Image (cartoon, rainbow over all chains, first blue to last red; front, top):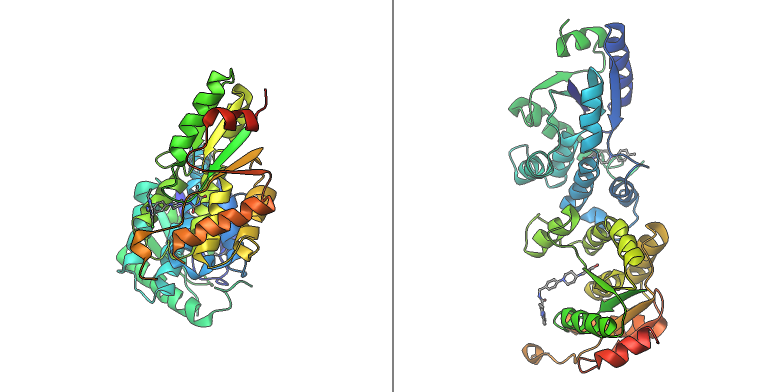
Length: 191
Length: 193
Ligand SMILES: CCC1NC2CC[C@@H](Cl)CN2C1C(=O)NCc1ccc(N2CCC(n3cc(C)c(=O)[nH]c3=O)CC2)cc1
């Protein structure tokens, strides 16, 4: 089972990944985790992150350029994701493809029905063959240049809610910060 | 020996690569060639090509984004270049890193001493470790464009940056030649008997 944890920067996804992995292990499942972007592990991920801190000229000013770099990072991880899915009962991704749709749409002042989210679906799932997640979990809540942009994060949160409501990329579950990890594990993979 | 053929669009680099390969082979050297970008052979190059046809939203409007895609294509080709260099006496590249510096600088209305050309050198050679060429051959051509008599244009600016890159020895030794260059004499200069 492939589970993606999604939400805006500062939502607390890493903590939820840690707590959810512990709940799955308490239920007897083997778990692997993988975080995107793969900073330190791929050139595309490193350049993209650096661009959001102001490096690399005009790169960050292009929404589709940034989205393309994050997609190329994920493309280099296809074999890794497939390997983890064959070897372990549950694979939890800290951020996945929906992050690219949410931030790209929000930067362009688009909604989940706009061109950017559809472009991400086409390039990442259809063209690059990224494994489709069984669950996308939105951690809904009330430093690089995205994180400093309060309006951007607010718009991204709204796009995320729309993506979940429209079933973008697969089945979604929406949870809050107070979600109980044990019950969530039971919902995602009933005993 | 690793040789990169450089020049503006329409200069005739592919023809020069073919003629130089024949001259090296007539001189007893084995030759392999590789063209950049590797259109049709790498995801990065294919997305770049699509953006050059107007696809992918605002991707092409970022000079550094396009330069990054061409660098990522080349990064994925290091194993190939190293293999060709182990297998053949001469490896000739139809465009290489200097293309990225020239077109990036020209698009930004910069010269060879500007930020884009230094950034290309920093990322492609110093950071990604791409093989540095033994020779970069600039196929220089007339900058006159009959369509631009209304007036420099992108191609004209790129040609000027190229001339500066060659004069300053950017990335290594350069040789500047014209379309009428004799392939045998050029081969003898690049790899003396
Ligand atoms: C042969 C086709 C043409 N002949 C002429 C003659 C005159 C003009 Cl004005 C325009 N021309 C043509 C033209 O513009 N065709 C359209 C055209 C032609 C070529 C390009 N690329 C040029 C190289 C460039 N590049 C390459 C590498 C390896 C790199 O690392 N970095 C980089 O940036 C990519 C774009 C784009 C559009």
